[PDB]
Image (spheres, coloured by chain):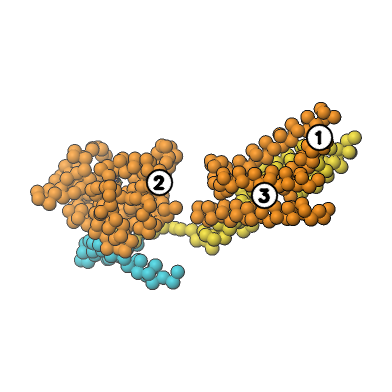
Chain colours: A orange, B yellow, C cyan
């Protein structure tokens, strides 16, 4: 039988250098306040020396947390260019109009406008159709080529190495904790550069609390990434408004465990119990229960409207024609 | 139970190992192929109203041939022009997008 | 899952090796070794 009790100071397990006193749960174990510690207590060397850790009941590590307009069709071909191509458009339908009494000019102006709406050997207007064709050929080629560069360049933070290779997206960790101290002491290639950046990054890329870090990621429009424990991260991803996600694998291999006073009777029993629970998939089941189960979490169109608009305009021109007749 | 295990020096688990005409349906989205077909018959039906039951079938097959892409009746005239400008943009988009795909090329 | 150093029940090397593994991991020596044989020594 057991009695669940919350640690006084509400800390995990650290050791004040001066007083050399343990605090939090790890403390209450060494000083006989409690018989066992069942919590997300990290298995560290500094603690394994004073207390006993059962096999990990949950492996984790450090992870990364990140967060139409029809005007994309008017950009490729500049508004100024759409204009001139229309001025030259009627500029050709008027030149052809001079090639071929008041109504006879209207029927013709509508025919040259149909010869305009794009697709004998009168040399005059002949070279006009040829030059106009070569003109539109260049333009449509330019539009196509230009539209490709905007799509080529248009073609995500996957791993940690991606954070070091770029600078556009800022990133940081908690101002105090094993997470920050990890990069500082890490002698690994990638993590080294990362720390060098965060160490002198301005403004401060470090946050006061975990809540502040998440808020910074949700308010930077994807310009700021936050590094934290995978466990807490995965949980955040399953919380409203569901605007955060973990990317890539963990940066290191850690693990929580059940802590028991050195040379305790519950030592071996609990250890085996953890192994038994994991093999029965009971541990994985529990996590799924509280993390996921209990969790809470254009351009082409613009050309379609101009088409239907043209169809409607025609359906209008049709009706009037039958009326006059 | 029989021996003693030190703390894990390497955490692991069970993973998945793996090694497509669907690279043609991607450039132009399935949703776009649909609408371009709806507007396709949407024009062959508008033209069909421009030109007894069989006479409508022969015409609907003629406007469907005027649909399957390539006098001065201003009405249906601007329809053919606007529809041409429409397909021009689409085929240009497909070409441009496919080029991006062939440049970067990143179940 | 997870691999570990196995030692006969009630051995003298028991506790020492256990702490050694924890020390190596915290010094990032374990991660370093893996990178050496998996990716660094890798052909891809
Ligand atoms: O034993 C420890 N277990 C811990 C477990 C967790 C959590 F994941 F929430 F369960 C956290 N957080 C991660 C996210 O930020 C808020 C709190 C900190 C822990 N710390 C402090 P560290 O010194 O920064 O590692 C320990 O010492």
**Label 3 crowd bin: few (<14), some (14–19), many (20+), radius 10 Å:** few
Question: Which corner quadrant of the image does residue B74 belong to?
Answer: top right
Residue B33 visible in the snapshot: no
In the rendered view, tell whether residue A119 sits above or below residue B41: below
* Circle 2 chain: A
What residue appears at the point 21 percent right and 40 percent down from the top-left corner? A10
Q: Quadrant of residue A190?
A: bottom left
Q: Is residue A74 left or right of residue B83?
A: left
Where does label 2 land, which residue? A222
- Tell me the tag on residue A103: 1
With respect to residue C44, does A314 lie above or below? above
Q: CA distance from mark 2 to mark 1?
A: 63 Å
Do marks 2 and 3 share a subunit?
no
Checking the image for residue B88, the label placed there is 3
Using residue A305 as the reference point, say whether residue A56 is left or right of it: left
Is disc 1 surrounded by few (<14), some (14 to 19) or many (20+) residues within 10 Å? Answer: few
Q: Where residue B45 appears, x then y in whole percent? A: 77, 38
Q: Please say whether residue A13 is visible from this viewpoint.
A: yes
Tags 2 and 1 touching, CB below 8 Å:
no
Residue A37 spot, x, y in % from top left: 24, 45
Task: Give the answer, above or below, for where B73 lies relative to C9.
Answer: above
Residue at x-position 66% and y-position 54%? A135
Is label 2 in contact with label 3 (beta carbons under 8 Å)? no
Q: Could you tell me which secondary element the residue under label 1 belongs to?
A: helix
The answer to whether residue A90 is left or right of residue A57 is right
């Amino acid at each position: 039988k057991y009695k669940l009790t919350i640690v006084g100071d509400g800390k995990y397990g650290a050791r004040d250098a001066d007083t050399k006193i343990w605090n939090g749960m790890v403390g209450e174990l060494v000083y006989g306040k409690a018989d066992i510690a069942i919590a997300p207590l990290t298995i560290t060397l500094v603690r394994e020396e004073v207390i006993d850790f059962s096999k990990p009941f949950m492996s984790l590590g450090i992870s990364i947390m990140i967060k139409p307009g029809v005007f994309s069709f008017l950009d490729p071909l500049a508004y100024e260019i759409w204009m001139c191509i229309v001025f030259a458009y009627i500029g050709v339908s008027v030149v052809l109009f001079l090639v071929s009494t008041n109504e006879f000019g209207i029927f013709n102006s509508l025919w040259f406008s149909l010869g305009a709406f794009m697709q004998p050997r009168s040399l005059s207007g002949r070279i006009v159709g040829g030059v106009w064709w070569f003109f539109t050929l260049i333009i449509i080629s330019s539009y196509t080529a230009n539209l490709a560069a905007f799509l080529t360049v248009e073609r995500p933070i996957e791993s940690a190495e991606d954070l070091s290779k770029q600078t556009e997206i800022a990133y940081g960790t908690l101002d105090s904790g094993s997470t920050k101290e990890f990069f500082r002491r890490s002698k690994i290639a990638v993590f080294d550069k990362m720390w060098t950046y965060m160490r002198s990054a301005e403004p401060s890329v470090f946050v006061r609390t975990t809540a502040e870090g998440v808020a910074r990621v949700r308010k930077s429009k994807g310009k700021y990434a936050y590094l934290l424990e995978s466990t807490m991260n995965e949980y955040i991803e399953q919380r409203k408004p569901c605007d955060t996600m973990k990317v890539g694998g963990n940066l290191d291999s850690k693990g929580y465990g059940i802590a028991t006073p050195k040379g305790s009777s519950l030592g071996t029993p609990v250890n085996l119990a953890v192994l038994k629970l994991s093999e029965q998939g009971l541990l994985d089941k529990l996590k799924n229960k509280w993390w996921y189960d209990k969790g809470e979490c254009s351009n082409v169109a613009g050309v379609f409207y101009i088409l239907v608009g043209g169809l409607g305009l025609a359906m209008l021109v049709a009706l009037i024609e039958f009326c006059y007749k």
